[PDB]
Structure formats: structure tokens, C-alpha cells
Image (cartoon, rainbow, N blue to C red; front, side, top):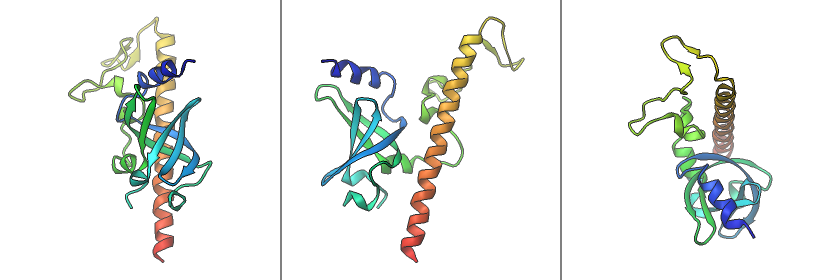
Length: 164
């Protein structure tokens, strides 16, 4: 089997702290399982489902945005947090949390793609493939942050309904 290898591949592509999309797959007494890639499913512990029984917060088939808090490749287990994703949410878009952590250095400065000239604000010639890849990653990061906005709006509308 190749489960160790699939999970290693996932980990080298979704560092700890990234906020990733998932589908709620099954509710267990101790959490909610979330499929984050084909073949890869992680557990959202009960104490991590919300800032405040799992059926209480999520249902099967729900799109969810979850923060990767741990990857244990020895036990082939991925730990996920809905609540910790929501804590990090800002209405202002930070692409580093949503799959572009590479475009930022250790201090948090932005790193332009190598083929792009910042003073010109134009791509140099010969970098079409680099550009298309950068544009796809960036479109994916936007898609994720939008999914996250929708989860925050869903959570707040439910509360307002509960509150009333």
C-alpha cells in the first residue's frame, strides 16, 4: 500500500497552519471526520469544532475550512481544527494562510515570482508557464478565503437565529 507516501505528499504540500478546504464525511461521538484530499481524511476533535454532539455544528456533506494543526506520519493521522481556522479569519485576504506561504519570507515580506519585474509591474519574457501557475495558485487561495468567509457568515447567521 501507499498510504504513508500519499500522506507524506500531502504534508509537503500543506504545511502546519494552512487553512484548507474539506468535506465533512462522518460524525463520530468524539469528533467530525473531514476529507481534505482524495484518500486523505482528518479528524476534527469535538473540542475544536467551534469557538463554542458534533451534529450541533456541522453536518455530513458540508464544505468546511479547517486549519491543519498536526500531521503525524508515524500513525498516519491528521489533526484539523475548525475553531482554530475561525480564530485566524480576517475579512482582509492574506494569501499565505491559504496555500501561498511560499510567496512570503521568514519576516513576512512578499517574494515576487522570479520572472516578474516589480518596478515594471510586468512579467519578463519567457515565463508564461510560471505565470499561469502563479495565477492558478492565487485563484485557488482566493477561492479558499471565500469559502472561509461563507463559513464565518454561516456560523454568525446561525447564532443570530439561535440567539433570537
